[PDB]
Image (cartoon, helix red, strand yellow):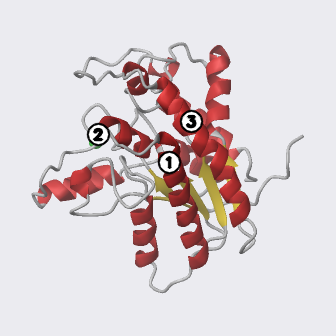
């Protein structure tokens, strides 16, 4: 049986990674290139739509359109749950991890008041895992998961302390079906990591609800994806595993039917999956 709808939303502040970014990695990397920062690359690049790491709007942009809300999207492609980014060359210029996004958002308010009606959307952790796998992190995956969860909890606590009262916290995605993870033969590693994050984060959200009357909504992206992938024809999908736009080891021409694909590139869903995710997220809120 469904719960009562939550209150209407008219402002979202989004924090996170490439699954949310609507143009910050593009704006920041053009700035970094214009200033000659060492190692800077133009992100996301020439096979991506309008600075999104996809072929269309991200889920949080769809959530904002469905709710009739303005969106301030702080998310940066590559962001980890702590201070920094998968792209280590960004650190010398800006701390673009979740903790850095929160810092910058609170610094851009004077001593000014966080809007207690705004929805603070948090969607991060994938790059904690991608950086560990790609650069041979020595932390056991269960410890990496605990770090990701502690960093998310810390961001919620800091935003709450500053005045935030409403949150939407997104689970880990199904990293085990991400094309790059499958090609790397890292499926069971991804499963252990994502299950540890997803088991522990709801326990931390219960603790945080004890304080400040926080509204801490949880979106289980794994439940969402498992349902879509088990019933793909219902949603017009056909190809669940191959990227529409290959980039590894090199760029190849995009598929002709991208709205029938789950994945855009080796890491990121298509606009169609972002649309379905944002509609699923919006279903808990009144208009
Ligand atoms: Cl562009």
| Residue under pointer 1 | 143
Label 3 CA crowd tier, 10 Å (few <14, some 14–19, many 20+): many
- The answer to whether mark 3 is within 8 Å of ligand 1 is no
Q: Please give the name of the residue rendered at 53% of the width and 64% of the height, measured from the top-left corner.
A: 155
Residue 182: give x, y in percent of width and height: 43, 21
Image mark count:
3
* Cα distance between the residues tagged 1 and 3: 33 Å
Assign a secondary structure to mark 1. helix
Viewer-proximal residue among 165 and 261: 165
Tell me where residue 279 appears, x and y as whole percent: 64, 39
Ligand 1 is found in the corner quadrant, namely top left
Quadrant in the rendering for residue 204: bottom right
Q: Is residue 123 above or below residue 195?
A: below
Q: Nearer the viewer, residue 101 or 6?
A: 101
Which one is closest to the eye, mark 2 or mark 1? 1
Quarter of the image for the N terminus: give it. top right
Do the CB atoms of the residues marked 1 and 3 lie less than 8 Å apart?
no
Counting residues from the start of the chain, the first of labels 1 and 3 encountered is 1
User: To which quarter of the image does residue 28 belong?
Assistant: bottom left
In three-dimensional space, the C-alpha distance between marks 2 and 1, rounded to whole angstroms, equals 16 Å
Circle 2 residue = 135
From the top left corner, tell me how far across and down residue 106 is, in percent: 46, 75
């Amino acid at each position: 049986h469904t719960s009562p709808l939550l209150a209407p939303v008219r402002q979202i502040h989004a924090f996170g990674d490439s699954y949310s970014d609507n143009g910050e990695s593009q704006r920041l990397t053009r700035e970094m290139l214009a200033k000659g920062i060492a190692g800077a690359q133009a992100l996301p690049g020439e096979v991506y739509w309008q600075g999104r790491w996809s072929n269309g709007p991200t889920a949080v942009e769809v959530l904002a359109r469905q709710l009739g809300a303005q969106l301030a999207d702080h998310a940066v492609g590559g962001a980890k749950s702590g201070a920094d980014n998968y792209y280590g060359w960004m650190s010398a210029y800006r701390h673009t991890g979740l903790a850095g996004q929160v810092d910058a958002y609170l610094a851009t308010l004077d001593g000014k008041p966080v809007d207690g009606q705004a929805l603070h959307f948090i969607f991060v952790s994938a790059n904690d895992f991608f950086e560990h796998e790609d650069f041979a992190g020595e932390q056991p995956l269960e410890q990496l998961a605990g770090s990701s969860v502690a960093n998310i909890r810390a961001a919620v606590q800091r935003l709450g302390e500053a005045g935030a009262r409403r949150f939407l916290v997104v689970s880990s995605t199904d990293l085990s079906v991400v094309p790059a993870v499958v090609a790397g033969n890292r499926v069971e590693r991804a499963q252990r990591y994502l299950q540890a994050v997803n088991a522990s984060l709801p326990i931390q959200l219960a603790a945080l609800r004890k304080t400040r009357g926080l509204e801490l909504s949880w979106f289980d992206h794994l439940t969402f994806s498992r349902h879509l992938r088990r019933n793909p024809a219902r949603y017009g999908l056909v190809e669940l595993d191959a990227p529409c736009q290959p980039t590894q080891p090199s760029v190849r021409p995009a598929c002709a039917n991208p709205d029938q694909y789950y994945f855009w590139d080796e890491w990121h869903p298509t606009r169609r999956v972002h649309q379905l995710a944002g509609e699923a997220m919006a279903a808990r809120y009144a208009r």
